[PDB]
């Protein structure tokens, strides 16, 4: 739910864009959001 | 840090970036960074360009620091390869646990065999991949 | 198809009108073909024409069965429209009854050909969406599969 609130739309926008802001958002997502998902995967 | 960068490597980097430093103050712009990366022999990626921009105008000593970081990454890869190769004392991909413990005891780091006994057990013959994973934790 | 759309709109309280207003809940598009613009009717017919052209491209030809050597059958009584000119009434509502062909069964080979043509049409729609995305910057759609 926390990811879907804000983080998931950012990831979707980054995926759609595939810019400096886009690169920064992608780096943020890959360094903060998905590590938590991997930790909570079990 | 620049100890990872070799004397020949830092000399070559300085020779390549002397053109950038010839501008008057060494303030290398994005175009100068692109030309320096092209002259380095490897095309920089988008992440590398973003990191250089964030660390920046960029400077010739900053280029030296980036080259030193790249050399450190190369040295880390070489150390990983050395851990994968040398640890296979048997040479068949499965090093003996006793041989690995003896090698660890007789090491420059002067590590304790009893202390690292649990790590050695976790890893009869310890696989080379298992030894590399244990070394890299 | 327009009659079916009008019936669905009537089920949703939407009705045909000269002007379409969201507050009035009236859809000008869901109107009879004669009442609506002739260009709209031609565009609607262009869908079936394009489907027939795609079928012909796949070597499939559909021709109306001639009324020859066919035994007569009983026909259910239904209202018959007078053969005279009709003028649309804006005040009068739309009460369409589109035909239903659930009882009629298509051929199995024709069903497979229709499935292939539907896949081709989905591919064409995905190509149009890809062109729109390229106008917007490009993207990947799971539908285009």
Image (cartoon, rainbow, N blue to C red):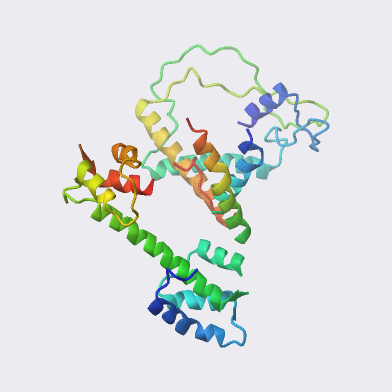
**Residue C30's x, y, as percent?**
70, 33
* Residue at 24%, 43% in the rendered image: B127
**Residue C122's x, y, as percent?**
48, 41
**Residue C114's x, y, as percent?**
42, 33
Front-most of residues C134 and B57: B57
* Residue at 58%, 76% in the rendered image: B59
| C55 lies left or right of C25 | left
Can residue A37 be seen?
A: yes
Please tell me in which quadrant of the rendered image residue C111 appears: top left
Query: Where does the C terminus of chain B fall, quadrant-wise?
Result: top left
| C15 lies left or right of B126 | right
Front-most of residues C70 and B47: B47
**Residue C8's x, y, as percent?**
67, 25
Please tell me in which quadrant of the rendered image residue C86 appears: top right
| Whether residue C71 is situated above or below residue C9 in the rendered picture | above
Can residue C42 be seen?
A: no
The count of marks equals 0
* Residue at 75%, 31% in the rendered image: C16
| Whether residue C31 is situated above or below residue A10 in the rendered picture | above
């Amino acid at each position: 739910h926390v990811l879907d609130v804000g983080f998931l739309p950012d990831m979707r926008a980054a995926a759609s864009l595939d810019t400096e802001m886009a690169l920064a958002l992608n780096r943020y997502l890959c360094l903060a959001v998905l590590p938590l998902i991997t930790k909570c995967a079990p | 840090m620049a100890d990872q960068l070799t004397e020949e490597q830092i000399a070559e980097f300085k020779e390549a970036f002397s053109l950038f430093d010839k501008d008057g103050d060494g303030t290398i712009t994005t175009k100068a960074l692109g030309t320096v990366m092209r002259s380095l022999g490897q095309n920089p990626t988008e992440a590398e360009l973003q990191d250089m921009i964030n660390e920046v105008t960029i400077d010739f000593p900053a280029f030296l620091t980036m080259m030193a970081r790249k050399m450190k990454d190369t040295d880390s890869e070489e150390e990983i390869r050395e851990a994968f190769r040398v640890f296979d004392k048997d040479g068949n991909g499965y090093i003996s646990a006793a041989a690995l413990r003896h090698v660890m005891t007789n090491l420059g780091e002067k590590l304790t065999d009893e202390e690292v006994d649990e790590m050695i057990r976790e890893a009869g013959q310890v696989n080379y991949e298992a030894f590399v994973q244990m070394m890299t934790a | 198809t327009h009659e079916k759309w009008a019936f669905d709109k009537i089920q949703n309280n939407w009705s045909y009108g000269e002007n379409v207003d969201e507050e009035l809940k009236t859809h000008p598009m869901l109107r009879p073909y004669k009442t609506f613009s002739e260009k709209d009717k031609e565009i609607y017919r262009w869908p079936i024409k394009e489907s027939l052209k795609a079928m012909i491209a796949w070597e499939w030809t559909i021709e109306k069965a001639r009324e020859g050597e066919e035994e007569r059958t009983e026909k259910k009584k239904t209202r018959k429209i007078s053969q005279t000119a009709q003028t649309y009434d804006p005040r009068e509502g739309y009460n369409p009854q589109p035909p239903d062909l659930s009882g009629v069964t298509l051929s199995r080979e024709l069903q497979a050909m229709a499935e292939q043509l539907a896949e081709n049409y989905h591919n064409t729609w995905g190509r149009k969406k890809k062109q729109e995305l390229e106008a917007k910057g490009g993207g990947t759609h799971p539908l285009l599969v």
